[PDB]
Image (cartoon, rainbow over all chains, first blue to last red; front, side, top):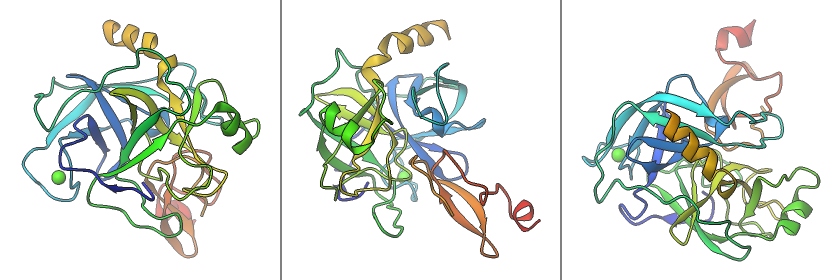
Amino acid sequence: IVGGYTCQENSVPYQVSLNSGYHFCGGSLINDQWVVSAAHCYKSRIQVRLGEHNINVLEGNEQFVNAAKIIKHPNFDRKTLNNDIMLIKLSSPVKLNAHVATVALPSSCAPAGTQCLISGWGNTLSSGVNEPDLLQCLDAPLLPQADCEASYPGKITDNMVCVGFLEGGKDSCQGDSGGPVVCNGELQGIVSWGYGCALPDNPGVYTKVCNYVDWIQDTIAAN
Amino acid sequence: PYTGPCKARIIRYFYNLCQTFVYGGCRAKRNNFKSAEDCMR
Ligand SMILES: [Ca+2]
């Protein structure tokens, strides 16, 4: 996250870190046994870390659970990133508490202009590299689809939504992928891609979660 | 090294000598290896 601020200790309880030796992607806890992330964050072996704030220090509130099932959307395109969404079933249910909680799936697609909260442990620099210890937060609005398309000519599908500022300055970055974009208590987006981080005319592109609620529920009930 | 448009944080190798860089997770170029040995070959 570039241009953000450190999130208040356990104010983002649904945020998880995907780890395979080191943190490589984020995710969101949607129920006591399922995590939702981006399909491009796929790995054959993944350990999910919940209750994290400082990913580099053992604080005492974290839960470490291995992924038992990793299911990517059947229509995921690694080239265009269309349908960049994936579900992870945990080895065992997690213990829900003040530091570890679930986030609600969308009731409907949020309109442009809606204010959202993006979070992650990704790069904080547009130029250079600075990996934070602490979880970063960023308040940003959902952009009109026309501005999204104008920023990325012919690269935006109906399953993508732009979030951020057309002037740059604030944006998600490498290490944020798979993370949450929550608007009014509902998960409306998943950090997916963008050209660089926080560059003008190139705001972040996110997977439109509201287009996958039924697929998500159907998959969870079948697995 | 080409990080790519995706925002994952995956460590990959690239030739300078063979060194590391953060790969985004998608649309990798040729100068992107999973190991140093394969990179030096
Ligand atoms: Ca920690």
